[PDB]
Length: 123
Ligand SMILES: [Cu+2]
Image 1: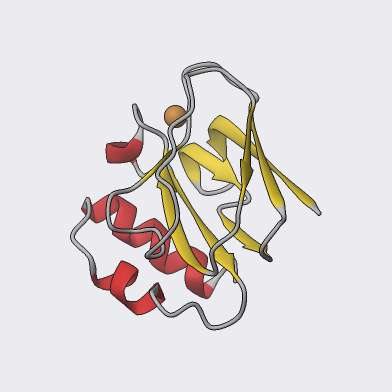
Image 2: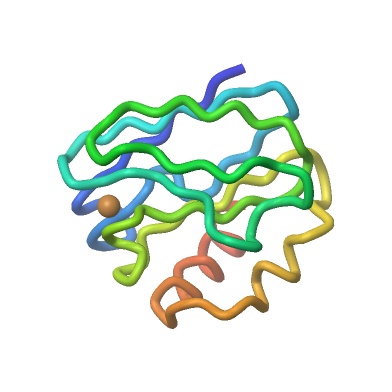
């Protein structure tokens, strides 16, 4: 099935956000990213996607449909606003093997704080 995500300049958690920021899906599902405001895109983060999944990067302002195949956790960012915290976590299948690794990886402090919130309060 399909899960729709919006990219906004301002939302429930503050400025520059993906809503929802926690996406639960299964292999074969699609995630459709819709920039409701301009200036946003979606890009997989290096070493924060599962082992055999392909990297991806959309163009700014375009609607992008991601098909997810490999199970595991994926942290995606908005390229321009990553440093301002704009990320989302996609969890494919149950108990994603790489989730603790992604939570521990090096990333901006603001990113880390939002990630921690979404895993607690968004799961
Ligand atoms: Cu953005």
